[PDB]
Length: 55
DNA sequence: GGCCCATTCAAG
DNA sequence: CTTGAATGGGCC
Image (tube, rainbow, N blue to C red; front, side, top):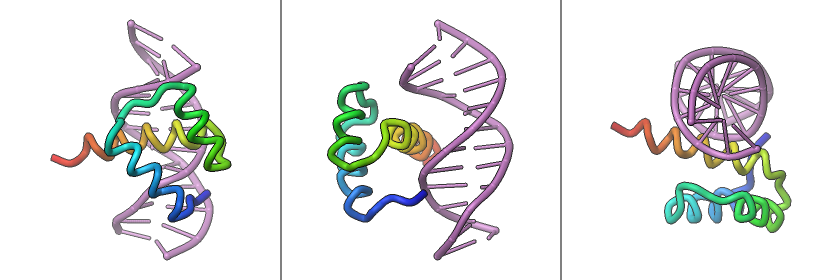
């Protein structure tokens, strides 16, 4: 799978301002991006890991 | 259930 | 080789 440049945008923007998202927030964010909840939740998790790594 | 973590695996 | 989406197990 691969995400659009359009998607990585709102995703990264949201992530920068909010590192933990609720169920509803993830689900709506997924809806307006025509993505599944799973891949968005997964993305966020992976991003949290990425954020951790930088040391 | 979600999160954490190590690990996997399909393209650049 | 790196990248990052995706997996499974362990924990609350």
